[PDB]
Image (cartoon, coloured by chain):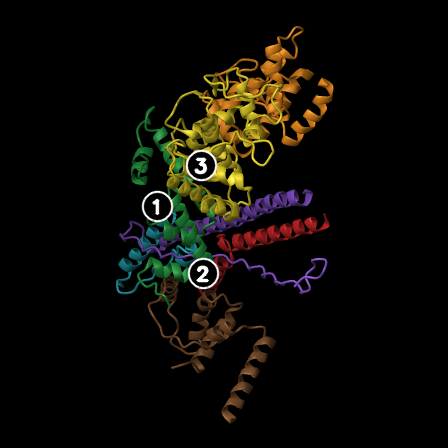
Chain colours: A red, B brown, C yellow, D orange, E green, F purple, G cyan
Amino acid sequence: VRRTATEMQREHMEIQQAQTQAQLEFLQRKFSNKALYSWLRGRLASIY
Amino acid sequence: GKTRQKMLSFLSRITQWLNTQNITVEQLMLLLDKISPAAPTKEMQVLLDLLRNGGIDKTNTKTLYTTMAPVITAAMQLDITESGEALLRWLDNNHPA
Amino acid sequence: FTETLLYRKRYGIDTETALMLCNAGISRISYDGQLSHFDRLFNNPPLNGVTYTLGGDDILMEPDAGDPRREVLKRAFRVDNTGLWQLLVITNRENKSKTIENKTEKLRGLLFVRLLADVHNLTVAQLDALLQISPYNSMNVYALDGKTRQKMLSFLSRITQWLNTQNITVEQLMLLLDKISPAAPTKEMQVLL
Amino acid sequence: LQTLSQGAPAGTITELYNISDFHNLINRCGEQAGTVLDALQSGTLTVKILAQALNLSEEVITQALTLAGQKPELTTWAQLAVLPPRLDLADTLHITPKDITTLLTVSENVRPFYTDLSALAGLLQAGLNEQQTKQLQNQSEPRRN
Amino acid sequence: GILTTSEARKLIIKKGQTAGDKEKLAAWCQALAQRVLVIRTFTLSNAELQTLSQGAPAGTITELYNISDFHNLINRCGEQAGTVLDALQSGTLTVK
Amino acid sequence: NLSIDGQPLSLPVFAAPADPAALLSAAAAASGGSKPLPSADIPAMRFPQALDSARSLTGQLMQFGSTLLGLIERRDAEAMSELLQNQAGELMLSSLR
Amino acid sequence: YRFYDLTAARCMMAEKAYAWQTNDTATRYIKSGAWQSNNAGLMAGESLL
């Protein structure tokens, strides 16, 4: 019983891994990411 | 007997150096690749359109760097505009042919 | 025989279930001194003390009807009142009859259709939806030769393993593949327009 | 709220029962409840779209509609409050909602016929497990002996 | 039977929308929502979408197999998938 | 190679398990060409007034751009706030299980 | 998006008024690249002004 509880702990850990990858993927695909503000920052620094 | 000796010493040194610097062999390959160019990308055409437009980059040196610097440091995702200013200097002082 | 070994190798089944997947009839005859597959399927125990014989002429599958032979079928194929009609739909979608006959081959066909869902870890509504996406829309279990059944089982195993790897269920795939058949637009539609 | 805003009676207990049943049904609808209440505010709520929302079969909701018969004309929310007790009772007994008017007519009869009594007995035994029907045989055979 | 978006623009600017050809536009939006669901059920990016936007067949199972295999390959590409789909949109994708 | 109880005298055939695979998703920079300039025509206002008339609308578009970046940023925060709650619910199911 | 097309033609009217009142049609000031589809046209009015 304790081994089939720790296998469920492993499955819980794998679904936390999948959720962390979904969060990273959301921060990369989104529009207001690092790249948008990077281009806007450099472009406004030039204009300024 | 001698150049094999030196070769094994070279491989041991580079392997221990890559383990201490926490970087793999493939990243070192990308550090040392000869370019052998091809057609530019669409992001390249964005970059060339953005430098081509905007203010004309000044013909005086040390002003060329500080005018070209913010778009280059945007295009490389570097931290500071002065870091991207000195990057053009470091590729200008020395670079492969 | 080699399909029986393969269908036992994957899915980890008993060999008689693999034979029932391999288009074999239900045996009335007791094998190695136990309850036969017909009797352990239907008469273990006999429902209300009624030994389910194959008397004939009277089984009706449409749910709003009263018949005592329907209940041993619902117990035997482990399915509810709508699902038994759904099995009769999956057996032949070109045959639109409501009744069946009480022969031993009709029970074999229904048992085959039930094991198609029970083996692949589907419910029978999921199998009904999953054979509409299939090239096996029009199928007959009583013209089912050895080759197209083989290919059908390979199709169902492939789509089931694909849905387990892609982390998406059967109902989401249904919504991916639904023909529209439109109706009146919503109020959010009128906002959009 | 806006479904209930156009004339839901509230002010006694047997009306809060109906409001709670309606709230239970719309929570079972879930993410697709918006088009259900949009169809109910219009005159276009059918059994097909509501079976699509509840993720139940169309041949189940049209059976629970026959109980307290309003059967094809789902135009008001008060006919939707009838559904969750019928669906819960057809869940806890693994039977269809058509399979329960026989329960209410035989199990409330004072002289039930033997054929209706057996046609309900095998009916309730059909939905059992294999372990459960073995336990039921172990309970039933000493009584008949 | 689903409208071209130019035909949808021609329909959506009319004098009066009839009893007909307004559930046609509703079926168009239902097909749009079905393709949105195709996009979200594989979690495909912008670049994978715009590669598939110029004529990826979807509408039967053996085409969703191909879309899932393409999504698997571009996930294996990973961070460098942008130049892969940029080369594929051009005529310069090589094996190297 | 068994003993008298049928127990194996050999050590069992070991098998070290596979390492868990690192997840990796496609990441692409957004691509987009610039928009060409609209055509020209001489106005009715002289330059000190037409310049002010253009400056008004360019300041208004600055206001629109700031408002639009605020709305994009705020939508993009709310979508993550809803994503975290969907993940917390489907993680709470596993914890209860 | 449809306001950028409004204000860019105003910038062009300003440039044509400048080119008419001082006869300098060779020079140009309102140049391209004000819209950038990577930014969805964000910070166009900054460059125009």
Q: Which residue is mark 1?
A: E57
Marks 1/3: CA–CA distance: 36 Å
Q: Which residue is mark 2?
A: E77
Tags 2 and 3 touching, CB below 8 Å: no
| Chain assignment, label 1 | E
The reply to whether residue D81 is visible in this rendering is yes
Q: Is residue C125 visible?
A: no
Q: Which mark is residue C32?
A: none
Residue lying at the far bottom of the rendered structure = B2
**Can you tell which mark lies on residue C23?**
3
Residue F63 position within the rendered picture, expressed as x and y whole percent measured from the top left: 47, 49
Q: Amino acid at mark 2?
A: Cys
Q: Looking at the rendering, in which quadrant would you find the N terminus of chain E?
A: top left
At label 1, which amino acid type do we have? Pro
What residue do we see at 26% from left, 65% from top?
A: G26
| Residue C39 % position (x, y) | 57, 28
Label 1 neighbourhood size at 10 Å, few (<14), some (14-19), many (20+)?
A: few
Q: Amino acid at mark 3?
A: Asn
B96 vs B76: above or below: below
